[PDB]
Image 1 (spheres, rainbow, N blue to C red):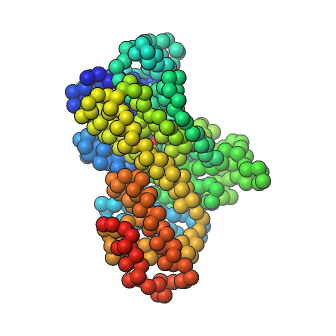
Image 2 (spheres, rainbow, N blue to C red):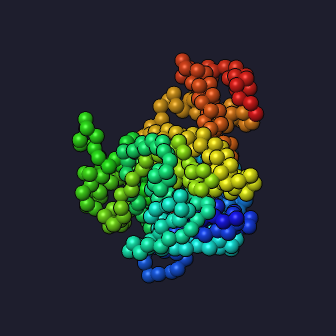
Image 3 (cartoon, rainbow, N blue to C red):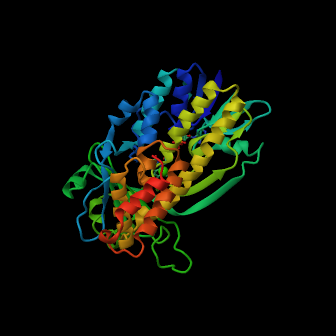
Amino acid sequence: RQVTIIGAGLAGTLVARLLARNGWQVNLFERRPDPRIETGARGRSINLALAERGAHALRLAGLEREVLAEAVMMRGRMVHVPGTPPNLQPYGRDDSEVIWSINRDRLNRILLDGAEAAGASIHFNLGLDSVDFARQRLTLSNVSGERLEKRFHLLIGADGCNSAVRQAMASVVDLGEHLETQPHGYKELQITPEASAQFNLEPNALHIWPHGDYMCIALPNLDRSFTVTLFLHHQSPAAQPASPSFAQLVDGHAARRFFQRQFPDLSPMLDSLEQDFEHHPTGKLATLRLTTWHVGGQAVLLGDAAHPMVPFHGQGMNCALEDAVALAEHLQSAADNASALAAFTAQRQPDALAIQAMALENYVEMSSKVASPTYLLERELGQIMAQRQPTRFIPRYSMVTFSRLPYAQAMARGQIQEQLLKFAVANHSDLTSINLDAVEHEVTRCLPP
Ligand SMILES: Cc1cc2nc3c(=O)[nH]c(=O)nc-3n(C[C@H](O)[C@H](O)[C@H](O)COP(=O)(O)OP(=O)(O)OC[C@H]3O[C@@H](n4cnc5c(N)ncnc54)[C@H](O)[C@@H]3O)c2cc1C
Ligand SMILES: [Ca+2]
């Protein structure tokens, strides 16, 4: 059985391994050069957060141990707000509930090796330009545009948030796209190993500097450096042209003054702020929803190609790897490819919609400069319900991050929990006046184990 995959990223490489291992003849085409060919170019420092959904996908693929050996454990959140050295907010009760910070390039290289070890053939420096579905032929080209045509039988679009496969499908079907732009851009910055140690930055934690309409995060690297991401509006809104935005930060010097004013405890840690600000490109964020993910039995999308989401829940890669497991499962045991692609789409679409929604919602959580007293009291009561009924009351962030519960169910159960806590806390200023056993009875009544 033959399959062509476009995009040797995270989902495309994993699905290539899973199919090749199961006897498929896999050809994988990648626009970029092979990152395993060492050059004299600058290293790639972006990292991301691997959680249970992605880890489990790697586990099934037999690659989890190799990946985790190069990942830094993040035990909890370190929230930096002015005047108060932070304390770790642990993610869970022990080190089984942690998130892993992994270098993106290293992860991609491990997956590339894994796909080839299973028998897939990978062809780099070839970007998909167009698809002729009627003649079953692809057109690819290198950076110079030197075209090259290939016959295909099954086409998997694993080619990212600006997928060319998706574009080609839109020529033969109505994808029913809903693009929702995000006002934040993002900028990568760096904290050196020396600086992070000088300022006693905890390596085994995810760090956040909330600031309302903008914020910075930092994820650790194995060498104690941190990769920092600034999230900030591209443009200053209409009824407030003075508020910060990338448009005001015309160069590295301006970025420094902005950081010294708004992130005074972080600015000293960013030695190369000016250079990194001007060198690294400002990224764009968006949510894109597709009614249609496949064309008959001929082509299917997965990962960012199928459902771009904002990065504020750290689940895009995790979702994409979950996608890859499901697609290989359906393709392996379906009656035919068309049946597989329809069943895969029907299964995954409700969950993709849910994590897209929860990711949007999580920005307020991350960027909030202070938690209202009514927020802390609900959280505290939720903690208590979790101890009495660890089988029933599980905070939504934990369901999303540390379990494989389908995203949609996690969102629905979170809704029940949110309303339960809200009514239970209203008109009570502290825990001592809340009828705790009544709350638990409501938990048991409304949340099945
Ligand atoms: C700032 C930011 C932070 C994030 N943090 C996290 C996080 O902490 N945790 C998490 O789980 N997710 C995170 N994400 C999301 C995550 O990066 C993506 O969801 C994930 O990379 C998607 O995997 P993918 O394989 O579908 O696409 P990609 O990993 O992007 O792979 C696509 C591949 O296709 C190639 N390609 C593109 N176009 C073509 C073409 N025309 N022809 C051939 N090849 C092509 C690309 O070069 C690339 O190799 C973050 C995203 C952003 C923007
Ligand atoms: Ca994400």
